[PDB]
Image (cartoon, grey):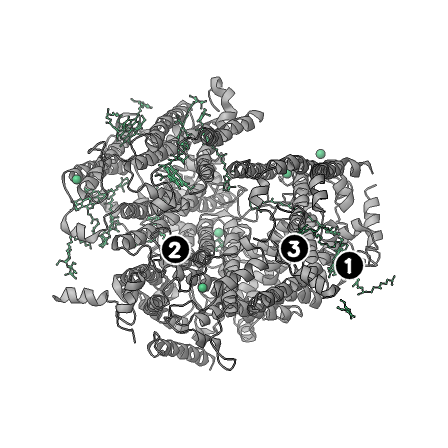
Amino acid sequence: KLPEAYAIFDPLVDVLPVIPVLFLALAFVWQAAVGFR
Amino acid sequence: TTGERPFSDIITSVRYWVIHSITIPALFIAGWLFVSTGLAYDVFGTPRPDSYYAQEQRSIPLVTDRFEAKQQVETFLEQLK
Amino acid sequence: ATNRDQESSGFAWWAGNARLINLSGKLLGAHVAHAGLIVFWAGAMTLFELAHFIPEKPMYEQGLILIPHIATLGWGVGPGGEVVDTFPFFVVGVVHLISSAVLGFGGVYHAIRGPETLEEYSSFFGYDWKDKNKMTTILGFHLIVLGIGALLLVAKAMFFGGLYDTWAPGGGDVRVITNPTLDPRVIFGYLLKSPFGGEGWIVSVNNLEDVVGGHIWIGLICIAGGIWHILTTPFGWARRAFIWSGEAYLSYSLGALSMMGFIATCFVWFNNTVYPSEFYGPTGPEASQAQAMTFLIRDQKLGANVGSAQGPTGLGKYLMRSPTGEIIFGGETMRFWDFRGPWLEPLRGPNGLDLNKIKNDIQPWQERRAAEYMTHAPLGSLNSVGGVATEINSVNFVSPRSWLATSHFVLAFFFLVGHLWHAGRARAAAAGFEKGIDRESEPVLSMPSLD
Amino acid sequence: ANLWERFCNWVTSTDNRLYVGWFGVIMIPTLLAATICFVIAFIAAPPVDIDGIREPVSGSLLYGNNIITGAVVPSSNAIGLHFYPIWEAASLDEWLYNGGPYQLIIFHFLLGASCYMGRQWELSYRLGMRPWICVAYSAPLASAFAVFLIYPIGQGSFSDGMPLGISGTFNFMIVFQAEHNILMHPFHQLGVAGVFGGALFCAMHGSLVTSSLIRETTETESANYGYKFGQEEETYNIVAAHGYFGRLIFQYASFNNSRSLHFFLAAWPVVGVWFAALGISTMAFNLNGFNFNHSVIDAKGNVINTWADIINRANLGMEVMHERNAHNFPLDLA
Amino acid sequence: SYPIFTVRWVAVHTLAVPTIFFLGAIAAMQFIQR
Amino acid sequence: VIAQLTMIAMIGIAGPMIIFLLAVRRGNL
Amino acid sequence: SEGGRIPLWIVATVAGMGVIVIVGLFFYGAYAGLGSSL
Amino acid sequence: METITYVFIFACIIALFFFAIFFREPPRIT
Amino acid sequence: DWRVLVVLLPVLLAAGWAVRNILPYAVKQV
Amino acid sequence: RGWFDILDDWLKRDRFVFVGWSGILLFPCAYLALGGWLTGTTFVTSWYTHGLASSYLEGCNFLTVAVSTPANSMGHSLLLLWGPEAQGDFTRWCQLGGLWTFIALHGAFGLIGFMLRQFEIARLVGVRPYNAIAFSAPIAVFVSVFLIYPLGQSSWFFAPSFGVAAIFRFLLFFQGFHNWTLNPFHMMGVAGVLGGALLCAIHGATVENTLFQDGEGASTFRAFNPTQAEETYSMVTANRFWSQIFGIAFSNKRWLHFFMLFVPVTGLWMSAIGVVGLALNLRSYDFISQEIRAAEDPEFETFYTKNLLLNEGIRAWMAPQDQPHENFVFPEEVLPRGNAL
Ligand code: CLA
Ligand code: CLA
Ligand code: CLA
Ligand code: CLA
Ligand SMILES: CC1=C(/C=C/C(C)=C/C=C/C(C)=C/C=C/C=C(C)/C=C/C=C(C)/C=C/C2=C(C)CCCC2(C)C)C(C)(C)CCC1
Ligand SMILES: CC1=C(/C=C/C(C)=C/C=C/C(C)=C/C=C/C=C(C)/C=C/C=C(C)/C=C/C2=C(C)CCCC2(C)C)C(C)(C)CCC1
Ligand SMILES: CC1=C(/C=C/C(C)=C/C=C/C(C)=C/C=C/C=C(C)/C=C/C=C(C)/C=C/C2=C(C)CCCC2(C)C)C(C)(C)CCC1
Ligand SMILES: CC1=C(/C=C/C(C)=C/C=C/C(C)=C/C=C/C=C(C)/C=C/C=C(C)/C=C/C2=C(C)CCCC2(C)C)C(C)(C)CCC1
Ligand SMILES: CCCCCCCCCCCCO[C@@H]1O[C@H](CO)[C@@H](O[C@H]2O[C@H](CO)[C@@H](O)[C@H](O)[C@H]2O)[C@H](O)[C@H]1O
Ligand SMILES: CCCCCCCS[C@@H]1O[C@H](CO)[C@@H](O)[C@H](O)[C@H]1O
Ligand code: OEY
Ligand SMILES: [Ca+2]
Ligand SMILES: [Ca+2]
Ligand SMILES: [Cl-]
Ligand SMILES: [Cl-]
Ligand SMILES: [Fe+2]
Ligand SMILES: [Mg+2]
């Protein structure tokens, strides 16, 4: 467990490791925005 | 092209979404309730978690007679008191 | 928007990063931002593990792969690998996470704000792929960096707490390395060992002195090599042997990384020194051996003479000989007799497993360890049901050794494929037929028929 | 030109009936050695103690086998992953008893096929071709590696490598299902999508192109004669073929671009088979198929079987029967 | 300029309507407890 | 268990939001 | 109404996110309630 | 006889490989 | 059965709504 | 130009989804087979026919849901909704396995419909009907496995059930009881499928790597025009490459593509013949010479006898739950087991 002081951020911490994956998806959103030119 | 309107047009049109922002959630909610009300169990004759066995029974209610199978299943269901 | 469509660049959206090949500033951006991705995952994953971490449960029962890495460096653990303080884990995580913000900042800047090319901005930072001199210089810088890293490991081991030593006398513990192995006969000796059974090449390194000395050597080699590559330009034979282009270099490094990936797969699967079983769980060999030990102990308690017990096949039920005669555990685990582990070695004598020691010297901690390792073998399902495929749901477990080995085999394979891809392409492009055959100059049409 | 130069020119010559090349320089002797040893062994090798329990299994024709049952039998469990070349044996008789032929053959062959891949790169380079046929070949190759090298490494013994024989292969598959539940593994499922799909697409392409052949012949001759080798004109009407297929499903489910289509034809089975290979290669380290044994449970807690539990029962039969004298302890850990 | 209720329209909806209903059901099922 | 979904909603939108804002402002996408 | 008013890239992004959500739910269900083995 | 038959068929197949390759009808461009 | 009306009320409300919204174009088409 | 011809006109209009006369058979049957599978796998049990849960509603996942075959006691009943078994009751009919016959029969007629569609469109567009002809292999497989095979056996129960894990079970059953891998017709099947996959792979990769440079782009797909007359890749270079790599090479494109039709189609047809044999337990189960030798000589061992031991395990350990109508009770002591396991 995290130090007690940081425990409030437990759900945030549970979600962070996935963020890199989102960048991959973002690349597609972005490409779709410029019509895959 | 074969005369129908391009899907690109339709799904990016405002009207399409006025319609379907209603019709899709409606359907979804309907299916949801079809389960939550328990209607699905009764329509399809599927056991609820407490209706696979009677309390001290451990024998599967397997159908063993072709022409009186219906009556068999019915008896099996009654056996759950 | 320079080079950002197929028309201007030649590359379709799905090969979009190929548009970055001669845009050194933007390419710099992509690289730094990616480095930020890696550092980000290190930190975030560490904090996730730490939040999900119960100290009195083995690490390997909790799906941890980073905290074990930190613990092996001697941070956070005491005798036997027991967690005595989680704070260092917290620090490693937080500091990586903070650092990733910096890297992502720099990467995003260079990628969509800074000079798109660096050559007109700075002769120091700019580069031409064909400029063999500059290429070997950048290579040099980075070699110096790597050497510095290996030396950081040395410094941790020798001057800042030491490393976790599963082989420490009296039991696994954190130990300061004071006499690292410097003798080149030993160090490169590892490199000249066969990769086959009972040898295992560098994967067989089984004491921390050899590891530390190894990194001393690697650090000096990398720094000297780096200076060398700064101060020289490729010799003629090298010039005539290689393809000199971005994609080619990428292909070389892809080959290297594929090799490294396979090597690491084997490392985490077999080695229990730099991957302590206390943190990573027993190796497959280890657990099989452990089963044999466990039932030898049980049966011998019941009054069985395990040295003379003849199994159904005629071979010893508990004990048999290796093909060269050493006494070893019987049953299928006969394949794993090259296994060595701190809990088994006290029973080993000059000719192998020692029957007197087996009869009189087996300690309770050994029974315990054998039972633990036997019941945490690296076998489990994709949805993390522990045990053989026929086991019923109940135990939530897949060994970290399995996760690490499988992941890195997959990555090493695809990286081999990437090497073939980009090597072949780099050849074709350098020779100039990567886009297809010239109809008016089709080479085969100018060749004699095969028959 | 000096002798070495001449020799290089020959080795890499584009005019040899069969291309040699530098990859060929390694490929030819290793493949020859693997081939010769394989044929001699398959005909005449004595029984081999595969599981290291002095229970020799007969693989050769002269020793009671036909084509379907025969095999070059994997090396002894006693050997594990030890390197067992001919000069490590006291004699050829010992070498044969312990399954030496298997190691000689699979090592020479893995090297030789690797060099076969490389050689495909090499010739593509000499002929001014694009380079990636070798990438397509990497899929069957990866598979070969998976069953002859990787799975043995992970399990700690070449005795668990796939046998060189038809029935031996089936043996391998069944034991594999027992211990890894490979059928329930998504990488094997992708492999099946790969070869079922490859088969589908093979038949589909073959039949669409055959269906759109341009009339160049009379009804008394083969239509094949309507194509001549090296003609610059295409031999079928892809517009007609696409009209057909696009109408069979709908227009945008069909390819109008031959390059895109052929790239699809290459990509689907190659990627699928890549995943098959990786499936074997990762079950090598016992990350197994999905386990939903006893996953469904009623309100009291009674187990409600699914088809997965029936699968489990079959696997159990395989598990308890396989290598019936080789285990002395309750868990089959490798 | 374009019709609305075509053969395509029907086809599409004979698939799409039940699909959304069904997904609603399966969703609900995820919260059933023994 | 609510804060997890809320968080991933904020992060998960943070991505598409950049694209959207830039598209509206006719930025250098 | 006129076609093209809502950007196809937005529609795609939203649709995709919905897909990920519903499938995410189904994988949640593999660990909770019926089918969880618990 | 079985062994002889199996090996004989195999031998014929190898010979066939040889003729199919070195004594094929040569492809000719038009 | 009240459950069939509670369940198939969203479906018929959707049908009625879209009928309301598409009625003029449907009449124009027919 | 009477009503028949007006109808023909309408059926053959060039719309987004072609209908045709064949569409009248095909679309309702394909829709009912698909919908039946989805209905069954979402909502319907297999408790009364197999003693199995098989739906999302019961807690199964994508891999374990199935529409299962009827009880063995139903024999080969068409199991019509209005038949003497269900007698019009939709719920009972579901409980008795009516959806299995529903799906298989509507499915069979749907496959007929689809092949008819292939003929119809080929005729309308002016191409030769080789696609339909190729589709005969899917037909042979479906009819041999889902219809003939159970018809040869005691009942629909031993047909494959429509589900992922259920199919996996079908496979394991065929190994254990039929020694199906030993069967030369299955082997020809495997050669056709793997050979088909190989042809797919190698042809695609070869075409892609003997392309002419027909554009300036490094992404080379755009450098093709569907209307173009010229071959887009070099058959001559392809031929020399494969000639020097493998010894032989295609030189005729027409033959190449016919061959690509021929291999997988033939494979599947052969596999069909084998399953038709297994309908009667007419197996390639054993080699009699093997068994005479092994019976007399307890040191004679091959992979063939090894695999039979595996089969024996499969039958004994799987039969009681896989065949509940038999009421098998195999006491612990009679279960075949090797040492320890
Ligand atoms: C590791 C993943 C990664 C990285 C680092 C890059 C990086 C890059 N890509 Mg590539 N790309 C990728 C994956 C990646 N790509 C993938 C997966 C695809 C397939 C979808 C592509 C397809 C592709 C194409 C077709 C093109 C690129 C291009 C580029 C470059 C220019 C981007 C640009 O100008 O857009 C502008 C984008 C915006 C204005 C939107 C915002 C983008 C920023 C970076 C988002 C930042 C988010 C982050 C959380 C902010 C943190 C702030 C904090 C640190 C303070 C850039 C160096 C282009 C190029 O080469 O130009 C020469 C180009 O044409 N990419
Ligand atoms: C990592 C690779 C890398 C490389 C090769 C470059 C290169 C460049 N940067 Mg970039 N940048 C980077 C990362 C990198 N940067 C990072 C991480 C950030 C976030 C802080 C930035 C943010 C940034 C901005 C805002 C600007 C640049 C600029 C420049 C250009 C001018 C450099 C200069 O003259 O500084 C002079 C050098 C020094 C003052 C010495 C630096 C002392 C270092 C930082 C001490 C630490 C060293 C140690 C090895 C760090 C290890 C980190 C590692 C563990 C991750 C040059 C092309 C400028 C530019 O492009 O102008 C047009 C510019 O304005 N960079
Ligand atoms: C990132 C690491 C790296 C990279 C990419 C390079 C790259 C290069 N080096 Mg450099 N070098 C390095 C680190 C590196 N070096 C270090 C750390 C040192 C100090 C030891 C040196 C000292 C050095 C010298 C003295 C020279 C180079 C040279 C070169 C150039 C040609 C080398 C070559 O042909 O390799 C290909 C390798 C060979 C041809 C070796 C023989 C081939 C056999 C078959 C290899 C078999 C290896 C086997 C598979 C490995 C298994 C394990 C093994 C222990 C058994 C090339 C640019 C040459 C040059 O041009 O300098 C300007 C040169 O003369 N390097
Ligand atoms: C063309 C499309 C088509 C085809 C080929 C089939 C075929 C089938 N359906 Mg399916 N079905 C369809 C569309 C189709 N269906 C549609 C659109 C629906 C929604 C209503 C259904 C709903 C449905 C259900 C609920 C069931 C079937 C079943 C069946 C099977 C038994 C049918 C039977 O015995 O009919 C008998 C009738 C005929 C063959 C009609 C021929 C009539 C002749 C040519 C004219 C003479 C009529 C005469 C004048 C009438 C006198 C009546 C008087 C004696 C009282 C059969 C495989 C059953 C099944 O699959 O069980 C497992 C079943 O339970 N179908
Ligand atoms: C270029 C490009 C790209 C990419 C990008 C990238 C890749 C970026 C990255 C970025 C990054 C890499 C970022 C990062 C960031 C980070 C951050 C921002 C962090 C922060 C942190 C914090 C705030 C912390 C907190 C805390 C503490 C301190 C304690 C503990 C707890 C907690 C966690 C709460 C793309 C593909 C899109 C496309 C276009 C182009
Ligand atoms: C740390 C450590 C250690 C150590 C280590 C070391 C010391 C290492 C070294 C290493 C090394 C020392 C390596 C090397 C490598 C090399 C390589 C890998 C090579 C490659 C090459 C190539 C690739 C080439 C190619 C070619 C050819 C062959 C022909 C011509 C052309 C070309 C050039 C292309 C030890 C174990 C003790 C312990 C643990 C820790
Ligand atoms: C560390 C930290 C942080 C940071 C964060 C970040 C760095 C974030 C980022 C984020 C992001 C970066 C996000 C993104 C997202 C994305 C998305 C969500 C996407 C999706 C996509 C999709 C869904 C797609 C779709 C599609 C299209 C578009 C087209 C094609 C087709 C498809 C359908 C595939 C904060 C500040 C919180 C603070 C605390 C700590
Ligand atoms: C049977 C029957 C019938 C019929 C009914 C029907 C016709 C139904 C239909 C139904 C339907 C029609 C349904 C549907 C459903 C759907 C679903 C349920 C879906 C889901 C999906 C998903 C889940 C997805 C997934 C995925 C994939 C696939 C890939 C991509 C990614 C993802 C993961 C997203 C009648 C009445 C006549 C009579 C009686 C019997
Ligand atoms: C077992 C590991 C062995 C490691 C060996 C490492 C050696 C490092 C230095 C290699 C020196 C290379 O020396 C290499 O050989 C001979 C020297 O006459 C040359 O020989 C070649 O030259 C030309 C080059 O176009 C060829 O067309 C010709 O066929 C051949 O004569 C090569 O062009 C040269 O580059
Ligand atoms: C690069 C970041 C370095 C941060 C500081 C690392 C201190 S490391 C510290 O050093 C002590 C001996 O000095 C050891 O006893 C202790 O166990 C160790 O954690
Ligand atoms: O499967 Mn089962 O697990 Ca791989 O070892 Mn243990 O028994 Mn044996 O050696 Mn061939 O086989
Ligand atoms: Ca330099
Ligand atoms: Ca309850
Ligand atoms: Cl076996
Ligand atoms: Cl054992
Ligand atoms: Fe083709
Ligand atoms: Mg659930």
Tell me which chain the residue with mark 2 is part of: J
Label 1: which residue? J79
- Find out if the beta carbon at label 3 lies less than 8 Å from the nearest ligand 8 atom: no
Q: Which amino acid does label 2 sit on?
A: Ala
Is I8 left, or right, of C101 in this rendering? right
Q: How far apart are marks 1 and 2 (CA)?
A: 57 Å
Query: Residue J304, labelled with which disc?
Result: none
Label 2: which residue? J223
- Find out if the beta carbon at label 2 lies less than 8 Å from the nearest ligand 16 atom: no
The x, y position of residue D309, in whole percent, is 63, 49
Which is more toward the observer, D16 or C416? D16
Q: Which amino acid does label 1 sit on?
A: Leu
- Find out if the beta carbon at label 1 lies less than 8 Å from the nearest ligand 4 atom: yes
Which is more toward the observer, D293 or G4? G4
First of labels 1, 3 by sequence position: 1
Q: Which quadrant of the render holds ligand 17? A: top right
Q: Which amino acid does label 3 sit on?
A: Phe
Label 3: which residue? J162
Which is more toward the observer, D84 or J214? J214
